[PDB]
Length: 23
Length: 49
Length: 17
Ligand SMILES: *[C@@H]1O[C@H](CO)[C@@H](O[C@@H]2O[C@H](CO)[C@@H](O)[C@H](O)[C@H]2NC(C)=O)[C@H](O)[C@H]1NC(C)=O
Ligand SMILES: *[C@@H]1O[C@H](CO)[C@@H](O[C@@H]2O[C@H](CO)[C@@H](O)[C@H](O)[C@H]2NC(C)=O)[C@H](O)[C@H]1NC(C)=O
Image (tube, rainbow over all chains, first blue to last red; front, side, top):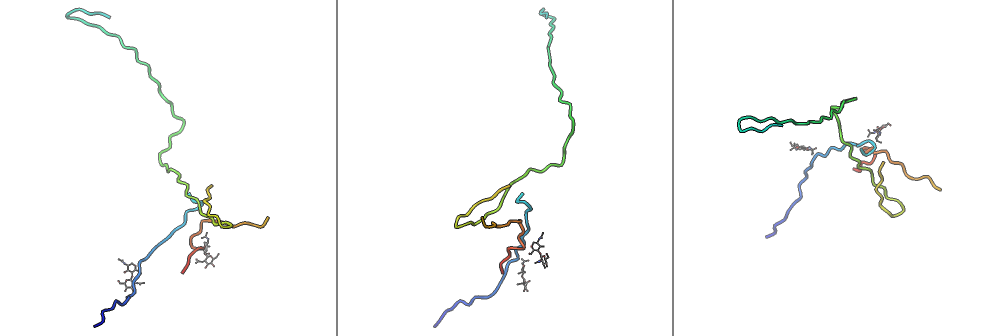
């Protein structure tokens, strides 16, 4: 007997935008 | 000013203050300063305009 | 007396892959 856990790929989309002058 | 059992009379003094506008502004936003972090000669520093 | 850093609030410039 030998139980194991194999990792399987995935992903989450992340958009980013700027803030001119930090305002 | 007069008080009978069948008749009365009163006077009231009202004073009004009317603001006359010069300009009216309708579409407005509030500013929120966030700034920027800077790591300098070991020290972390928050910088703002 | 050295020149110091520059900041311009550009996110794209600081992307790490
Ligand atoms: C969120 O965006 C990700 C991008 O990583 C989407 O991932 C894709 O999903 C499909 C299945 O519908 C896969 O066939 C693709 O290979 C994935 N693309 C990749 C890894 O670039 C994901 O579907 C999106 N999620 C939602 C809930 O819309
Ligand atoms: C913000 O940063 C990005 C990345 O440094 C700049 O976009 C690049 O602009 C040059 C031309 O100046 C192009 O040759 C590159 O292909 C661009 N790279 C990418 C990933 O788009 C951008 O010009 C900077 N400034 C502003 C105001 O957005």
